[PDB]
Amino acid sequence: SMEVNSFSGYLKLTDNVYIKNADIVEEAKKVKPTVVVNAANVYLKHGGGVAGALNKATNNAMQVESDDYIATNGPLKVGGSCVLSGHNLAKHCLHVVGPNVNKGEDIQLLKSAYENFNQHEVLLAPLLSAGIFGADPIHSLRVCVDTVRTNVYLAVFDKNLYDKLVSSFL
Ligand SMILES: COC(=O)c1c(NC(=O)[C@@H]2CCCC[C@H]2C(=O)O)sc2c1CCCCCC2
Image (tube, rainbow, N blue to C red):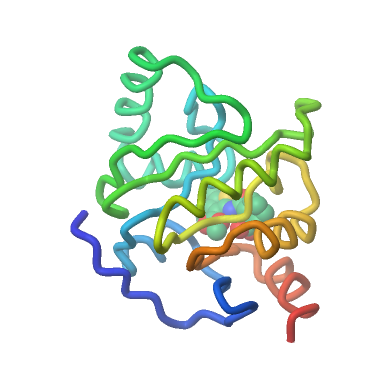
């Protein structure tokens, strides 16, 4: 999609981190960001969590693009990223691999994962390594705030989690 970056309705947590209680698919469609972040795995298999939602919204175009990327380039590393099409959601999708602590992956790589955001002026993003990836979402938000130095607009879907997360910044 042509970029518009129509961001509104966010709470400002820090100079550069904004957060909203939102479905990232519905938010991406309304914002048309330059970059939407996917909570990816190294083979870009878009199943549970944010990844399946973004892919479903593209009617599997993201998965077919991702399979072709993997065929040519092979898998990412944990903490790594690649830039692919944003399809109908964004100009670009930055597929970022946070460590999956459910799979015994090194939580220290969450810093590396969030560093990928710093390659981009502005992003719409979910929390990395939490949810199906098994890390504490409070820790994910802390690493995001400490590591991301560019303009990041966070969407958190679950209202109860959103309220608990933002409580410590109000
Ligand atoms: C912004 O996040 C989303 O919009 C979605 C998910 N977010 C998560 O899983 C986050 C993992 C990290 C911890 C925070 C979590 C959260 O944002 O609450 S899953 C998902 C969606 C799309 C909406 C439909 C529901 C099922 C597909």
